[PDB]
Image 1 (cartoon, one colour):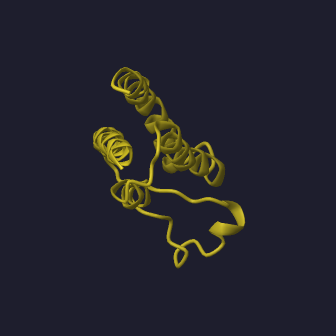
Image 2 (tube, rainbow, N blue to C red):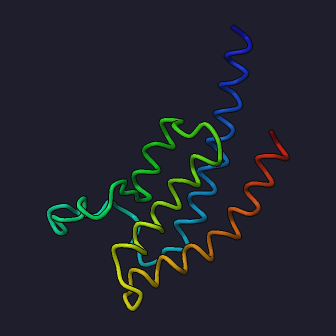
Length: 121
């Protein structure tokens, strides 16, 4: 149907805007701490601690599969990255400190992105 195609044109434009958003957020991680999943070879106990791991590479694979139906879903994943890190790692570590910075720097980007999604439907 023509309705189905129209919905698909909106998903596609959402996906375009979320790719820009993602790139902007990943820039706030110049060290690339959050770029890839945590290695279970290097942190074998990780899943005893963290039930839903997330990372930018995993968000990207979902994104290009148009796996994000709205901005909420995408924010949930971005918050997992941050929230997982701040649980596993202690306050005085480079990892926790990098999460805090990403969260603060990300919130600006996500503040305007929520306006563009509402604005452009």
